[PDB]
Length: 156
Length: 117
Image 1 (tube, chains in turn brown, green):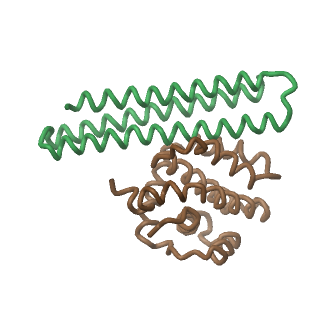
Image 2 (cartoon, one colour):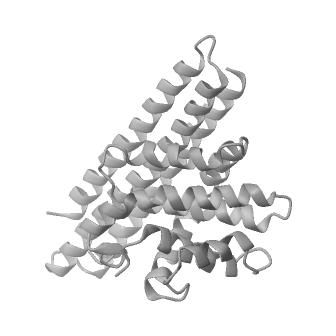
Image 3 (cartoon, helix red, strand yellow):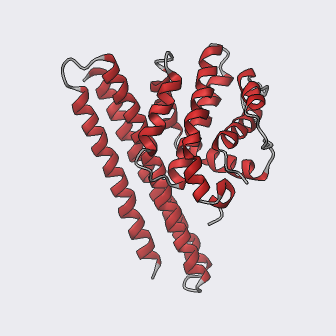
């Protein structure tokens, strides 16, 4: 019953945090998990499966992800608004697909990864980014619902 | 109906997808070269660039996924053997890697032109 994009992205970010940098979980992510509240385990089978797909996407498109992210983060003032802006730019027509979703979620996870590992990123930047990605991503909920949830979506 | 038809339909879709991104980035450049573009207008173009790059990656992923599913259906119907199934999926992967490179380089070219006009 994986019908919450906020929860699956949050659980994916937490799983990713264990595989990267110094391992330890950024307090922004711990607070997001408490507030949601996050009911998915970072070890749930659906999180594990998506994590494998998102990692492949990040590896295959690493140059593009680095370069788009770098251009994104040059302006940190309104990161929360800009995440919504990019999300809505991709999906506003109301024609989502598995690949568009996966690209988006891969991009978000990559961002979190780049932000949380770097000791020279200010707290408030990490906070706005996480809050921004999670809030923007809730836009996929209605579409994922129609598809029978995140779990059903990769069955085909 | 056969491996060449699966691979051909996917190649055209990945080329179509790649062409759509090239055209989007050309539109964005033309906007970027307008006079009295303000800082908000510039930022809006940067965000549209990111969205285009993401939509291209997602759309390539879709085309190839679909082709692989259609390849599976051939194997399940007994219309290709193991060799031919794997050979087909190998070819679909090369196609994905080639499309992915062209998309990457369209983005690079855009960024460089945005920096200096």
